[PDB]
Image 1 (cartoon, rainbow, N blue to C red):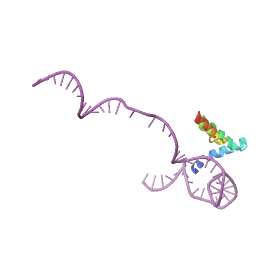
Image 2 (cartoon, chains in turn red, cyan; image 1 turned 180 degrees about the vertical axis):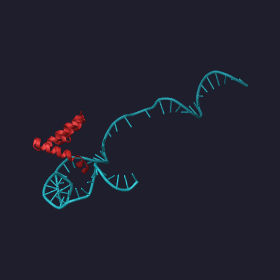
Image 3 (cartoon, rainbow, N blue to C red; image 1 turned 90 degrees about the horizontal axis):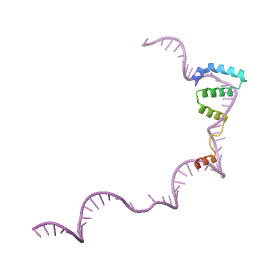
Length: 73
DNA sequence: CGGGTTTTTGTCTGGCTTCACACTTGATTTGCATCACTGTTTAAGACAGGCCAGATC
């Protein structure tokens, strides 16, 4: 952890200054879409969409009507 | 060869943070057992008498 901190502090300062100046310090959504598109580049739409969900926040499970629909159909 | 340059760690004392967590008590959920009910014979194959029928002395 400390290892990768050292390894990447240069990119850290780079991206933080550039994103803070560009969009007004909203590094959250900037880096969000950054990693989204970067991971989609290698055709990981599965992981990209589940990460879109995890950040969006929604429906980890199902509600009883849907489970009933499944075991009936 | 043993000595020296990387990655990797310890490391600072502050203020920050999210969140587990104390301590009841009943209203829920969830796990795991029970429960009552269903199918409605043979089919090949070995051995033994027993009866009869045809052979034989």
